[PDB]
Image: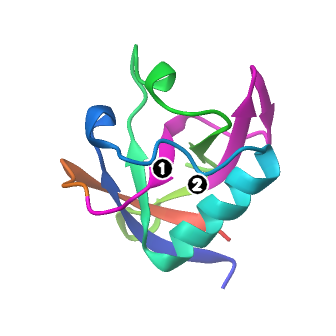
Amino acid sequence: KTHVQLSLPVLQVRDVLVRGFGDSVEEVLSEARQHLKDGTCGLVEVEKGVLPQLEQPYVFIKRSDAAPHGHVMVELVAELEGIQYGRSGETLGVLVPHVGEIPVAYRKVLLRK
């Protein structure tokens, strides 16, 4: 399927144990997609002070369209030293590995895969 319904656990930035997916734009997008498929991907909502507490390159989910079954359609955009790889809508948050942190909420998304 071109899209997959996912419910992403929303994590507090200070709880996150693994603060990024890797060391290159290509690796972080690769790893993010793998973790999204394996159900091991968390989401941190972006506010003042959040991104400096996480490791670059960043992987964002961004709204790709204006929401089937409550699932917002999103796509992945990576960011490294202020340059984004991909073009999309409003940031829903920054993706991180999930390794058993307790979420505060769930974000239903339809991921363009």
Query: Mark on residue 17?
Result: none
View extreme (bottom): residue: 1
Residue 29: horizontal and vertical position, in percent?
71, 55
Q: Which residues are drawn in magenta?
A: 75-100
Q: Is residue 21 above or below residue 93?
A: below
Please name whichever residue, 11 or 14, is drawn nearer the observer in this view of the structure: 14
Q: Quadrant of residue 42?
A: bottom left
Residue 45 appears left or right of 87: left
Q: Is residue 111 above or below residue 37?
A: above
Badge 2: residue crowd in 10 Å (few <14, some 14–19, many ≥20): many
For the image shown, how many numbered marks are present on the structure?
2
Q: Give the Cα distance between marks 1 and 2.
A: 16 Å
Q: Is residue 101 above or below residue 37?
A: above
Q: What element carries label 1?
A: strand
Residue 89 is inside the magenta segment: yes
Would you say the magenta stretch is mainly helix, strand or loop? strand
- Which one is closest to the eye, mark 1 or mark 2? 1
Give the residue number, with chain letter if any, for mark 2.
74
Q: Residues at badges 1 and 2 in contact (C-beta under 8 Å)?
A: no
Residue drawn at point x = 52 percent, y = 66 percent: 110
Mark positioned earlier in the residue sequence (1 or 2):
2
Q: Quadrant of residue 108?
A: bottom left
Residue 69 is inside the magenta segment: no
Give the residue number, with chain letter if any, for mark 1.
96
Q: Is residue 71 above or below residue 64?
A: below
Q: How is the image coloured?
A: rainbow
Q: What residue type is labelled 2?
A: Val
Q: In which quarter of the image is residue 33?
A: bottom right
Q: Is mark 2 on a helix, strand or loop?
A: strand
Residue 106: horizontal and vertical position, in percent?
27, 57
Residue drawn at point x = 36 percent, y = 47 percent: 17
